[PDB]
Image (cartoon, rainbow, N blue to C red; front, side, top):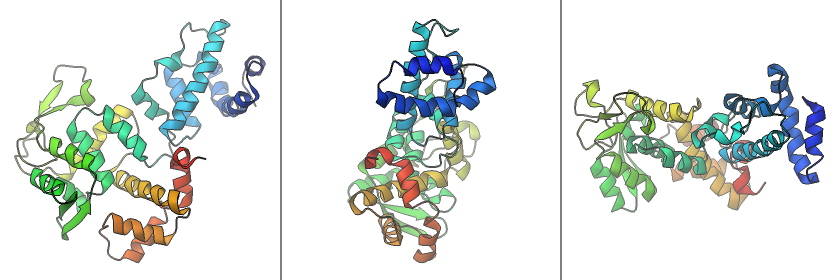
Length: 321
């Protein structure tokens, strides 16, 4: 059950019963990875700590943090006994962005709180806007609502109870209520002239690139030579790629960010209501004014992600579980 058991038990013996309770499962799940490298956690590299935590299949940044702090404690104890080959605690060198890399590979959806933490670390308004706008529902066929979104629509929405009028390439107009944060973000994205590469830590020569000048919230790079009009769908995917590369996560797609917003709404309704059923799903369709062929078909598709299991998993902490 444990690797280097003698030493773990020596550490466990110093802990309160409640701390033993949290630590034992960590050491148990850790064994397979410790045996693979033939070394203890306290000898793991940074990269191995991130891999270790990833192997625990944890779903939220909140939980990843708690786990990292617990491991950090153990490592400090190990250093103080001179057991570690290393003199420094490598869990404490883990950056905020690198927490994201500890997320389990089953993770599909971001929570509202993770969206906000992600947004805050993203220096380009293009990045902030695409993440946020997708989460709140502006999408459409091949992201046509997002790609066609102008400064003017954003301005009008602020003066119209935050109801954006969105344009889809297929089905045309649709009204969607969004947060004031989303609108202000979009407003800034629409007037951005430069885009910092590698989320503002670009190593080499070209640290920033010029954006095309227009009134669209989503903007093509000048170097693409696609001209002054609407960006293509590939720009959306390129911007999510840049976000994903900074956080080093592989779950983030336009569909996944859209669904995350639905999932957050599901949590809000679940907190007051206590169930997630078709009535909750119909309500989510309504609240996002969701573009669907039929509502019942959409409600059926939503069973794959708008359900109690998914909500309990992603929103454990906020639900008090």
